[PDB]
Length: 186
Image (cartoon, rainbow, N blue to C red; front, side):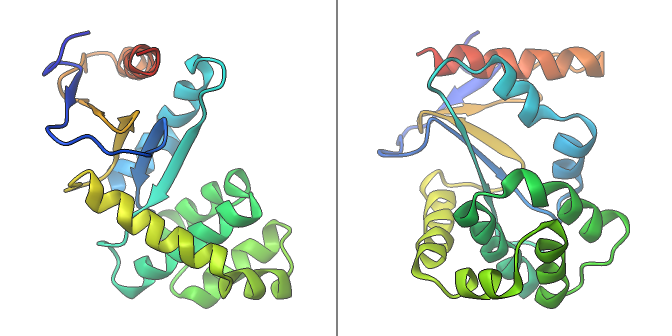
C-alpha cells in the first residue's frame, strides 16, 4: 500500500473527523453499484479492526431540493438509528422503481420500515437532525469533496479506486476493504 496508488493523503487533514467516513448520494449510479450491487460498505466493515466503526453521509449537490431533502431524511435515519432499515428501499425507490419523487414519498418509506409518522415528523424538525444536516454539509466541504462515491480514513487519507486492480470485479472489492483495513490500522 503506497501513497498515490491505492490511496492518497490530503494536504490539509480534517481534525475531529470520523474514523471511516463515506460519502454517497441516492441519485448517483456509481453509488448504486457501490453498495446495492458490489456491496463495498459491508465488505469494509467485515475487515474493520475492533473499535473502528464506519459513518455514511449523504451529499446534496444532486437531485435538486429533493437531494437537499434526502440528506435531511438521511439525518433522520441516523438520529433514530435506522440506517440499515432505509438504505436499500431508498436506493431502489429513487433509481430503480423510481417511486420516490418527493419528501412525502420518502416519509412513506420510513413509515413502511417501522417508524411512526409522528416520530418521523418530530425528528424531521428536531435540532439533532439540524446538527446532522449541517454536520454532513460541513464534512463534505472539509475534505474539499468534488464527487461521490468516496471514502476517507481518519480524516487524512482518501481512498483511490481506479488506482487499484479492476480486472476481476470480485477482487477489486476485496482490495478496497483491505486498503481501508490497512489505513485504519494507522
